[PDB]
Amino acid sequence: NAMVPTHHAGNGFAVASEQGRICALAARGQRDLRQCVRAYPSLFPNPPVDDTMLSALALSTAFIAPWCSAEQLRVANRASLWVTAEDWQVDRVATSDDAVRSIVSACQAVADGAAPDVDCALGQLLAEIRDELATGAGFTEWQPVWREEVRRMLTADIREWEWRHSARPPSFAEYLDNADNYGASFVNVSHWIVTGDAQTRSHLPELIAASREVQRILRLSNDLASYERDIRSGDLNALLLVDREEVSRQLRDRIRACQDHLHALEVTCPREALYLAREAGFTTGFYHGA
Amino acid sequence: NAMVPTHHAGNGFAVASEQGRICALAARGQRDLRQCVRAYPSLFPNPPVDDTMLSALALSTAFIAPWCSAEQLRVANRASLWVTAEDWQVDRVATSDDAVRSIVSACQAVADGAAPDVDCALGQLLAEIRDELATGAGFTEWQPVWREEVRRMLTADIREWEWRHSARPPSFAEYLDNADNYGASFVNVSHWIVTGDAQTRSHLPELIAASREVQRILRLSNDLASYERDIRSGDLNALLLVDREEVSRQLRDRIRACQDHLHALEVTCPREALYLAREAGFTTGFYHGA
Ligand SMILES: [Mg+2]
Ligand SMILES: [Mg+2]
Ligand SMILES: [Mg+2]
Ligand SMILES: [Mg+2]
Ligand SMILES: [Mg+2]
Ligand SMILES: [Mg+2]
């Protein structure tokens, strides 16, 4: 026990002071989330989307990238909201194989630059985000990268809708392969487009592979936390495909592998790696809620 | 620059994971805050008390004592709420020199064990907290200590009400001497009664002197953040008595002196000192909001 420090108040003060500054940062970010729910209240019903949910969202993006101002976090926050609006339109609103695919097609069209249909709130919010990226981009030729993340996420949403209505569930491995429907990579790439530079662009392929590794971690941590809810709605959950012991051991090992990659990656992408490490850290700790 | 570490993702993950666990802890604490606002809605009007305010409160107590469960933070949270209910009844509701003093007398009476009057919501909430302390106390003879903090806080509320209606303002020094009206020491002592032990009791005098030192820091940091609001309501504010430069230099030096005391104090009160250091850290960082 003598190797364990006797004094902790000094570091205690310093850590708590940064946690307090980030909580105020998150409160400032919550203001744009409210603005967004307001412009499109049809996407954000109350029974799910209340200021409690908006608070948790703003706390996550502030604690994931605490070096950003609230204005710099605008995109990450609205993209995160857009993912939850799109999830809802697909999981709850859609009632047909045809309904889901027209949503997907309409979003892809907007992501590719088409004007949103006037009756399509989901498409109008995406078009707003896309135009924010166009004005805010720190580098050119961001469009192919962003459209690809849109495509990957929407395609995976299709596959999950099919699984919920299919005769046989996917394997655990196949399910984890489908984690783009979580939307984390979509959010990360949106964030990096407005906050990165030319250096960011030349490292985008590696950054996106790391982002997809973190997203698999987030899917496992999400599902371990949401098992009861998922059971309740017939939604797919990793713990239906393997047991909690395998999910937890795999979470542990994936985290340790991912941090080894981030350790290498930070030599070239210090800000990028940090963003991902804090995204994996905050989200797994928050979802676990120990 | 080579002395500055190249690698930050690993520590980034670990810090973010604890921040995420504490944010979930805070969300669990918010549930008792809601329960309390509900039982006494007459004390907690909406124009001030919304879930935004409750969220900030729960985040502060969770980040100040992250080793506590939500159940262990119940008292600290309800005592904090009680201070804001009492502030409101005094600042807004009371309209007379007589009104303020009967509030004070009624609260002191409940703190000393009297039954609250059936028409007195403020007194009923205090009686609930007092009874929670009685059942939850980690040591005997807590009552004289707690009643003294009640008395100090209420007496200072009287003095501030008089200053707002007096011909001459206090000096800066006298104002800072009156910081018990902030309620931080009241909250800390309530917290320590239910979470401390016999060891805590024998160190209470020193712990309370340290608590009062942190409270002066909190008053300065509060006032630097609330200057505009205070100007708006004619409420007293340290920046009316000295200039921002002196308040800021004094905040800096008081913090450094207080952490020197906490450094000594932690040898005997490790958990106590930590609580105070994190209270000073979180609150000054949150109020500053850089
Ligand atoms: Mg979904
Ligand atoms: Mg999803
Ligand atoms: Mg879920
Ligand atoms: Mg007051
Ligand atoms: Mg006060
Ligand atoms: Mg104030």
Image (cartoon, coloured by chain):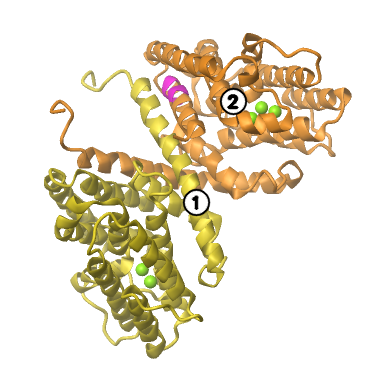
Chain colours: A orange, B yellow
Q: Residue at x 39, y 20 (%)?
A: A270
Q: Residue at x 70, y 12 (%)?
A: A170
Same chain for mark 1 and mark 2? The answer is no
Indicate left or right for A8 with A136 as reference: left
Chain assignment, label 2: A
Q: Is residue A50 shown to the viewer in this render?
A: yes
Give the residue type that dot 2 points to: Asp
- Would you call the spot at circle 1 few (<14 residues within 10 Å), some (14-19), or many (20 or more)? many
In the picture of the structure, the residue carrying the numbered disc 1 is: B30
Out of B180 and A124, give the one closest to the viewer.
B180
Indicate left or right for A32 with B126 as reference: right
Q: Secondary structure at mark 1?
A: helix
The residue segment tinted magenta is A273-277
Q: Residue at x 41, y 16 (%)?
A: A259
Question: Which quadrant would residue B168 be assigned to in this image?
Answer: bottom left
In the picture of the structure, the residue carrying the numbered disc 2 is: A223
Q: Residue at x 65, y 19 (%)?
A: A240
The answer for how far apart the CA atoms under marks 1 and 2 are is 24 Å
